[PDB]
Image (cartoon, coloured by chain):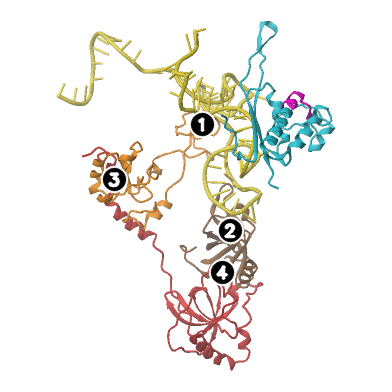
Chain colours: A brown, B red, C orange, D cyan, E yellow
RNA sequence: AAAACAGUGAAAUUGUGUGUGGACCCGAAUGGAUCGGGCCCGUCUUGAAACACGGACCAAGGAGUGCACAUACACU
C-alpha cells in the first residue's frame, strides 16, 4: 500500500510542524498566508535559518490531490513561529494538521 | 465603408497589441536558479526526494544545468544510476577517490511518483563497470559496506541546523 | 473549437486566467422575487450599501475597468464582427490579423453554405462555423 | 392522448389515468404516498383493512392537529386516519389494473406499483352567508390521478 | 359591467423524480467537521434595527406635459 510507504519515506527525512492559524488581526483574516510552529525551534534567531525552505501538506484521504506544496516566507513574532504560502488557500477544516519541512530551498515562483 | 466595420471595429487600434504582449511575457518569465559549488566528485550524499529518498549514494557529475548524476550500489543497496535536481541532495563530509572515464546519462527521479519499482531490475555494462570501480574503494574500509545499507534518519529531539554532516 | 490568434499564442492563458468573475447583483434581489438582478444604484437615506459599511457588498465603478489593450478580446485572442452577407466578409480583408466573423442568428442554412465557402478562400475565421449546419 | 409524468416501457407495464374526480386532494395524496413501491396484491389487501377500521393511513405532510392512534406504530409514527371516500376510489382503480394485466398476458403476481401521482384540478365555486350581512367562499377541491405498475425482474 | 383568434403559452403557486442544505447575502477554502464580516427595506427627522408609519405573494397599468407673453444662453 503506497500511502503507508510514502509516509515512512517522508518521516525519515523532514522536520515536523503544525498549522495553527491564518494571518489575522483582532477582526479580519488574510487567508493567503498561514502560520506554522516547528518542533524544537524556539527563538527568532533560530527560526531565521528556515526562511526559504519548502513545505508539504500530505493528505491521503483526499480524492482530488494527495499533496499541496508551499514555501516559508518570513519569521513571525519572538518565539520561533513562521509564515508560509501554498499553491492553494488552506481551509479552516485543515487547521491543527501536521506539516513537513523539507530541508532544501526553492524560489517563490515554483511553489 | 460597410456599416458593420465603421462602428464595431472602431473600439481599438489592435495594431498596438504586439508591444503589450512582449511586456507581459517579460514580467511573468521565471527567475534564475543558481548552480551550487559545494559538491565534489565522489562526495557521498543523501537523497531527499522521490522513490529513492533516505538512501546514501555517490555523486558523479553535473549534467544539464541543475541536473546531477548519481550512483547507488546495485549489490549493496540495489539503487542503480540516475539523474536528479542538485538541490534534492544533502551533502556529507565523506569523499571517495573515484574518477570516471566518460560521460553517461540516465532517467530522471521526479518529485511526484505513483508506484514503486519492486521488480524488473537489470544492469548495463556501464552500471556494472561503475559499481566494480566504486566497490574497490568500499571493500577496504571498516564498516563502510554496512553504512550504505541502513537508511538515514533525522534526529527528532534537536534542531536540524545544530547537527553536522 | 481549439484555435488561437498566432500573435498572442504564448500569452493567451495568462490573459484568460486574469479576467475577473465578479458579479454586481442589485441589493436585496435575493430577498424578493419582484426585484431583478440588474444593477441599480441605491439612493435611500439609511441604506447600508450606499454608506459603504464593512460587510455590505461592493458597488461598480471606474477602478474595475480593464486595460485598453486586453478589453473586448474573446478567449481565442480575436475581436468579433457581425456578418449577414457575402459582401460583408469583403470588409475584413485588411483586418484578418486581429478580427474574426460571427454570422447573425437569423441567416438560414442555404445562405450559410455560401458564406462559409467564401470564408475559406479569403482566409477568415468564423466562430459559429458548425452552427445549425451540423445535420 | 396523455403525457404520463415519467418514462417506462409499454411492454411489461400497465397504466390508467383520470381527470377531475371529486375526491378531496389533500386526503388522496396521503393515501397514494403509503402504497408507493408496494406489490399490487399487498396494496389491495391493505386497503380492505382500512375500510374495516382494522388498519390506518399514516399522515406526514397534511397532518396538523390530527389524532394519535395505536395502528400508526406499523409505520413508526403516532398519527393516523381513516379516509373512507378516497380509499374506495383507489381500491377500484387498482383492481381494474389486475384485469388489464391478466388480459395483456402478464402474470397476476410480481406486479409492483412503480409510479403514482396526484395533481390539483380547478376549484368548483360555492358560498355561505355570514353575520353582519357578509358572504364568504365555500369551494370544492377535486383532483387528477395517474398510476403505472411494472413486472419485477427478480 | 365583463367577454377577440377553438395561435404562442411567462411569473406567482402545486405534485413526482434527482441532487444540495437548515433564514439568507458578501469574502476564502476542504475528502470532511466550516472560519471571518454583516440588524429590514422605503420615508419624514438633530437622530431609525427600533416598543415610529407603509409593505402577504406575482403579472400588467401607473406621476414635470401642451399653449400664450416677456427673458438669459448655444446654434443659423
User: Mark 4 or 1, which is nearer the eye?
Assistant: 4
Where is mark 2, residue-wise?
A35
SS at mark 4 in the image: strand
| Residue sitting at the far top | D133
Residues at discs 4 and 1 both on one chain: no
Quickly name the residue at label 4: A102
Instruction: Tell me the subunit letter for badge 3.
Output: B
What number is the disc on residue D22?
none
Q: Residues within 10 Å of mark 1 (few under 14, many from 20)?
A: few
Residue D154, how many percent across, how many down? 71, 48
Local packing at callout 2 (Cα closer than 10 Å; few below 14, some 14-19, many 20+) is many
Return the chain for callout 4: A
- Rendered view: B125 above or below A16: below
Which residue is pictured at 47% across the width and 66% down the height? Answer: A107
| Spatial separation of the CA atoms under disc 1 and disc 3 | 39 Å
Label 2: element kind: strand
Secondary structure category for the residue under label 1: loop
Spatial CA distance of label 1 from label 2 is: 38 Å
Mark on residue B12?
3
Amino acid at each position: 500500500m503506497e500511502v503507508i510507504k510514502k509516509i515512512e519515506l517522508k518521516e525519515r527525512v523532514c522536520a515536523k510542524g503544525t498549522l495553527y492559524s491564518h494571518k489575522r488581526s483582532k477582526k479580519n483574516i488574510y487567508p493567503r498566508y498561514s502560520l506554522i510552529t516547528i518542533e524544537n525551534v524556539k527563538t527568532r534567531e533560530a527560526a531565521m535559518k528556515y526562511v526559504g525552505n519548502a513545505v508539504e501538506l500530505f493528505k491521503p484521504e483526499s480524492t482530488k490531490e494527495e499533496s499541496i506544496h508551499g514555501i516559508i516566507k518570513a519569521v513571525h513574532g519572538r518565539s520561533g513561529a513562521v509564515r508560509a504560502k501554498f499553491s492553494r488557500n488552506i481551509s479552516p477544516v485543515e487547521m491543527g494538521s501536521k506539516v513537513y519541512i523539507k530541508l532544501y530551498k526553492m524560489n517563490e515562483d515554483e511553489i | 465603408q460597410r456599416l458593420n466595420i465603421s462602428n464595431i471595429k472602431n473600439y481599438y487600434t489592435a495594431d498596438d497589441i504586439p508591444a503589450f504582449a512582449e511586456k507581459l511575457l517579460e514580467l511573468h518569465k521565471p527567475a534564475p536558479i543558481e548552480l551550487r559549488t559545494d559538491l565534489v566528485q565522489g562526495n557521498v550524499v543523501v537523497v531527499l526526494e522521490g522513490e529513492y529518498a533516505s538512501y546514501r549514494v555517490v555523486y558523479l557529475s553535473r549534467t544539464e544545468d541543475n541536473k546531477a548524476l548519481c550512483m547507488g550500489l546495485p549489490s549493496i543497496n540495489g539503487i542503480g544510476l540516475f539523474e536528479i535536481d542538485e538541490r534534492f541532495l544533502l551533502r556529507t563530509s565523506i569523499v571517495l577517490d573515484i574518477r570516471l572515464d566518460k560521460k553517461y546519462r540516465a532517467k530522471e527521479s521526479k518529485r511526484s511518483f505513483k508506484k514503486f519499482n519492486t521488480k524488473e531490475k537489470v544492469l548495463t555494462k556501464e552500471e556494472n563497470d561503475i559499481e566494480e570501480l566504486l566497490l574497490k574503494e568500499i571493500e577496504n574500509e571498516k564498516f563502510m559496506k554496512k553504512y550504505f545499507e541502513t537508511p538515514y534518519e533525522i534526529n527528532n529531539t534537536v534542531d536540524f541546523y545544530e547537527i553536522n554532516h | 473549437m481549439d484555435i488561437v490568434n498566432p500573435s498572442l499564442s504564448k500569452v493567451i492563458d495568462i490573459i484568460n486566467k486574469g479576467k475577473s468573475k465578479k458579479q454586481f447583483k442589485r441589493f436585496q434581489s435575493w430577498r424578493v422575487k419582484r426585484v431583478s438582478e440588474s444593477w441599480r444604484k441605491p439612493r435611500g437615506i439609511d441604506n447600508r450599501m450606499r454608506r459603504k459599511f464593512g460587510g455590505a457588498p461592493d458597488m461598480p465603478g471606474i477602478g474595475y475597468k480593464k486595460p485598453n489593450a486586453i478589453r473586448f478580446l474573446l478567449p481565442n485572442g480575436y475581436r468579433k464582427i457581425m456578418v449577414a452577407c457575402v459582401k460583408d466578409l469583403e470588409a475584413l480583408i485588411s483586418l484578418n490579423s486581429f478580427y474574426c466573423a460571427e454570422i447573425r442568428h437569423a441567416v438560414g442554412s442555404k445562405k450559410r453554405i455560401e458564406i462559409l465557402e467564401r470564408a475559406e478562400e479569403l482566409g477568415i475565421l468564423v466562430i459559429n462555423k458548425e452552427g445549425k449546419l451540423v445535420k | 392522448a396523455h403525457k404520463y409524468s415519467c418514462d417506462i416501457s409499454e411492454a411489461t407495464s400497465v397504466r390508467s389515468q383520470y381527470n377531475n374526480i371529486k375526491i378531496k386532494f389533500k386526503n388522496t395524496r396521503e393515501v397514494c404516498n403509503i402504497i408507493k413501491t408496494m406489490e399490487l396484491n399487498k396494496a389491495i389487501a391493505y386497503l380492505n383493512d382500512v375500510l374495516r377500521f382494522k388498519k390506518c393511513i399514516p399522515v406526514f405532510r397534511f397532518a396538523k392537529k390530527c389524532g394519535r392512534t395505536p395502528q400508526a406504530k406499523e409505520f413508526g409514527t403516532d398519527k393516523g386516519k381513516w379516509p373512507v371516500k378516497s380509499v374506495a376510489f383507489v381500491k377500484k382503480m387498482l383492481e381494474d389494473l389486475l384485469v388489464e394485466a391478466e388480459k395483456k398476458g402478464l402474470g397476476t403476481s410480481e406486479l409492483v406499483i412503480k409510479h403514482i401521482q396526484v395533481n390539483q384540478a380547478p376549484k368548483i365555486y360555492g358560498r355561505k352567508h355570514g353575520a353582519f350581512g357578509r358572504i364568504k367562499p365555500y369551494n370544492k377541491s377535486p383532483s387528477h390521478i395517474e398510476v403505472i405498475a411494472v413486472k419485477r425482474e427478480h
